[PDB]
């Protein structure tokens, strides 16, 4: 199995073709790193898919938060309905990352809830990498996290076929060995028939937990359901219901080794400190040890992963990247944000666990169960393509120039930008807002301080304007509920501190004021300004007013870059006879 087949109603237009073709040629010529400098509004995902389709490579796509990853998932499901599209997120984006606050002497327990749906896809994702080569997995930063090993997974595989002879209680045990998927209560699970022709309905095998259930009748298996049969199979392969499954024999040795260190660190801890002496871990360690030799698992098994794997201390973890074939493709979405996040994962994780080993709530060995360092992420890269409108320094330095893709299909342009003085900035901006109102268009205003905004908001009302808010964290449900309100005429202007807040792309917005354009801050950086300038590119009369006293380096670059893109798009609309017009959108609701 190995054929990618991209299904789109439309076709590569604007400047995708050169971008696709160029990226594709860089893959084949063997370039390690490439960058897709693409403006929002162009068909960024479609372009990436086309690349994928053309090279026929199993690929991982890295989003930097639960939502974007989800968005690429559905989108990429659509582009590839007849292929292996997977979702690999985790519980890293929620639940207490078990740590300890010394000063406040207040312990936090790993308190999480396995959202079963995820687990399904994790497992279907981890399985598919062994069935077909036509696989695409969307994932968060989690993909660089400590997972089980890959071979001791492909190795713990229960291969079922017709003609082969296996007890009705042999396969039953080869099954419990792998932390049993559908071998328990709710019912006899897979118990029925028996003999040299049994029932065995291997149902909840998480890598298909959306009612699939494989039923095999002594080498004579066929897919089924919660109702009845469907699609007859000759060969089926079951995957370990867990990512961290260890063979009894290795577990017996790991248990010893844990002990040789739960002990020998007590000797080193005894001599040095007097933190409960050293001891105090005994309650959960020995508790966990007993829970391991009396049952394959235990509380937070993850913490023993290096031991269970039987590898040397300091060893580099096993991760989703290691489940992939030797020559996969990685695509980093919003790479100017995703990469920095990725690289800061280890420090943060080590910090929060160094402490846990200090109040002896975990042993040193627990430090070996962590995310990858950036250097280790690099060493595991075969070939990557970074996607971003404003690529970071790592992407630009490691890739040979950039592959551009700035032409949107409606020919909408990057806005014009005016930079004006701060003296009179408020009455000046009001004039410009009133006009937008008359023309039936909305403004978006950004300030640096959360109190200069409050100030401005109230000022605008005093001018008789339908102003938006001031509060940064106004939930997520009342947020989507104010945007909608703004793109309907409820309000005309909208004041926020951070306009990079996902969900502000609004075709009715024609003006964007930036109030302390030349002030230091993350949100006034070169990349941040360009990203903000882009909130006025969704409209044919898009304009940007920057209020400032000076032209910073950040402002220069941003202004020069927008200009360069606008000229280019304008010439393209000229050579092709396109007249810029605003993409309409449906005003839905909640
Ligand atoms: Zn053309
Ligand atoms: Zn380098």
Image: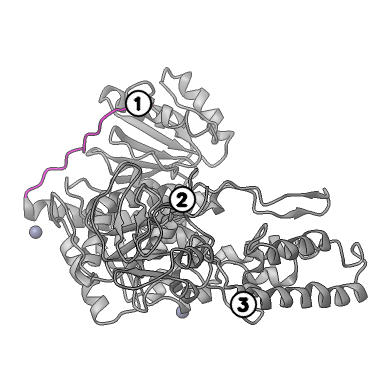
Near mark 3 (Cα within 10 A), the count class, few <14, some 14-19 or many ≥20, is some
As drawn, which residue projects farthest toward the front? Answer: 195
The tag on residue 398 is none
Mark 1: is the Cβ under 8 angstroms from ligand 1?
A: no
Which residue position is annotated with label 2? 189
Mark 2: secondary structure = loop
| Disc 3 secondary structure class | helix
Q: Is residue 195 above or below residue 587?
A: below
Residue drawn 33% across and 67% down?
59
- Above or below for 160 versus 526: below
Q: Earlier in the sequence, mark 1 or mark 2?
A: 2
SS at mark 1 in the image: loop
The answer to whether residue 73 is magenta is: no
Q: Report the side of 523 relative to 61 (left or right).
A: right
User: Can residue 62 be seen in this snapshot?
Assistant: no
> Where is residue 279 shown, x and y percent of the image?
87, 65
Q: Main secondary structure of the magenta part?
A: loop
Mark 2 crowdedness (10 Å alpha carbons): few <14, some 14-19, many ≥20: some
Q: For mark 1, what is the residue?
A: 589
Which span of residues is magenta-colored?
577-590
Contact, mark 1 vs mark 2 (Cβ under 8 Å):
no
Q: Which residue is mark 3?
A: 250
Q: Nearer the viewer, residue 522 or 295?
A: 295
Q: Residue at x 57, y 77 (%)?
A: 316
State whether residue 536 is above or below residue 11: above
Work out how far the residue at label 3 is from the one at label 1, CA to CA, in angstroms.
Answer: 55 Å
- Left of 301 or right of it: where is 404? left
């Amino acid at each position: 199995e190995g054929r990618f087949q991209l299904v789109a109603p439309y076709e590569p237009q604007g400047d995708q073709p050169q971008a696709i073709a160029k990226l594709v040629d860089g893959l084949r010529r063997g370039v390690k790193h490439q960058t897709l400098l693409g403006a929002t509004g162009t068909g960024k995902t479609f372009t990436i898919s086309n690349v994928i389709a053309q090279v026929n490579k199993p690929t991982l796509v890295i989003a930097h938060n639960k939502t974007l990853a989800g968005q690429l998932y559905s989108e990429l499901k659509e582009f590839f309905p007849h292929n292996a599209v997977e979702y690999f997120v985790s519980y890293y984006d929620y639940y207490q990352p078990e740590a300890y606050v010394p000063q406040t002497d207040t312990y936090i327990e790993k308190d999480a809830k396995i959202n079963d749906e995820i687990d399904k896809l994790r497992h279907s994702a981890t399985s598919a990498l062994f069935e077909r080569r036509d696989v695409i997995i969307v994932a968060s930063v989690s993909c660089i996290y400590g997972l089980g090993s890959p071979e001791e997974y492909r190795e713990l595989v229960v291969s079922l076929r017709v003609g082969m002879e296996i007890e009705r209680n042999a396969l039953l045990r080869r099954l419990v060995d792998i932390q049993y998927d559908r071998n328990d209560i709710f019912r006899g699970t897979f118990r029925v028939r028996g003999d040299v022709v049994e029932i065995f309905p291997a149902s909840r095998d998480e890598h298909c937990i959306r009612v699939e259930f494989f039923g095999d009748e002594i080498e004579a298996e066929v897919d089924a359901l919660t109702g009845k049969v469907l699609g007859e199979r000759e060969h089926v392969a079951i995957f370990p219901a867990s990512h961290f499954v260890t063979r009894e024999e290795k577990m017996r040795l790991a248990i010893q080794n844990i002990e040789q260190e739960l002990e020998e660190r007590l000797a080193e801890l005894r001599a040095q400190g007097k933190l409960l002496e050293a001891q105090r871990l005994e309650q959960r360690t020995r508790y966990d040890l007993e829970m391991m030799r009396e049952m394959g698992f235990c509380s937070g098994i993850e913490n023993y992963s290096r031991h269970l794997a039987l590898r040397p201390p300091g060893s580099t973890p096993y991760t989703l990247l290691d489940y992939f074939p030797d020559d996969f493709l990685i695509i980093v979405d919003e790479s100017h944000v995703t990469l920095p996040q990725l690289r800061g994962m280890y420090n943060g994780d080590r910090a929060r666990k160094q402490v846990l080993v200090d109040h002896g709530f975990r042993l040193p060995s627990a430090l070996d169960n962590r995310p990858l360092t950036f250097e280790e992420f690099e060493q595991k890269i075969n070939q990557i393509i970074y996607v971003s409108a404003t690529p970071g320094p790592y992407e630009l330095e490691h890739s040979p120039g950039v592959v551009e893709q700035i032409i949107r299909p409606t020919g909408l342009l990057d806005p014009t930008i005016d930079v004006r003085p701060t003296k009179g900035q408020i009455d000046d901006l009001i004039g410009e807002i009133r006009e937008r109102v008359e023309r039936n268009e909305r403004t978006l205003v950004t300030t640096l301080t959360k109190k200069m905004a409050e100030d401005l908001t109230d000022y605008l009302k005093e001018a008789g304007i339908k102003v938006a808010y001031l509060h940064s964290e106004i939930k997520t449900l009342e947020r989507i509920e104010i945007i909608r309100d703004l793109r309907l005429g409820k309000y005309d202007v909208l004041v926020g501190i951070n306009l990079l807040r996902e969900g502000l792309d609004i075709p009715e917005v024609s003006l964007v004021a930036i109030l302390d354009a030349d002030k230091e801050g993350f949100l006034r950086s070169e990349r941040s300004l360009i990203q903000t300038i882009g909130r006025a590119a969704r409209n044919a009369n898009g304009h940007v007013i920057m209020y400032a006293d000076t032209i910073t380096k950040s402002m220069e670059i941003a202004i020069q870059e927008t200009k360069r893109r606008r000229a280019i798009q304008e010439e393209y609309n000229r050579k092709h006879g396109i007249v810029p017009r605003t993409v309409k959108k449906e005003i839905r609701d909640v």
